Image 1 (cartoon, rainbow, N blue to C red):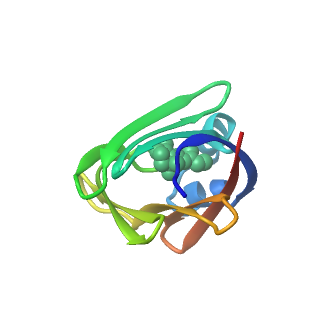
Image 2: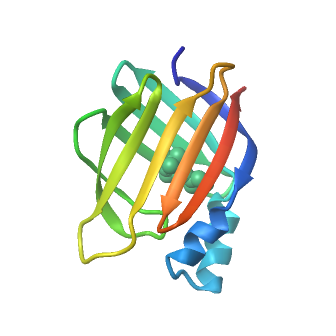
Length: 137
Ligand SMILES: *C/C=C(C)/C=C/C1=C(C)CCCC1(C)C
């Protein structure tokens, strides 16, 4: 199995709560939920090298990384971080995020495949766990 595809969302839990537990105010949460609550996910995987694009009608975000090599991106509440992805187990990867400036509650994300070929995204912030589920288009 592998992660490449244009993945369509079928479930999304607790995205706004991830923002709220990080202290993002209601104004800013409305803007983030409107732009990114239920994005499509496009992945191009070549072994350990990844391109991932999340998109809605109004916002696209793209990252490029290789497992085991540091890269820069932003946390879900918009703070710059340095990220590092590792395989937790076969076809489950976990991204550790370290803030570039100051401190804050821990954030992470995970992408994994189920035995039937669904893609499960987990995002964490403090004690909140957001789950999004996708199938290939
Ligand atoms: C609602 C979920 C997101 C907006 C997740 C975003 C995201 C990125 C912007 C980088 C690819 C990793 C991933 C966590 C899928």
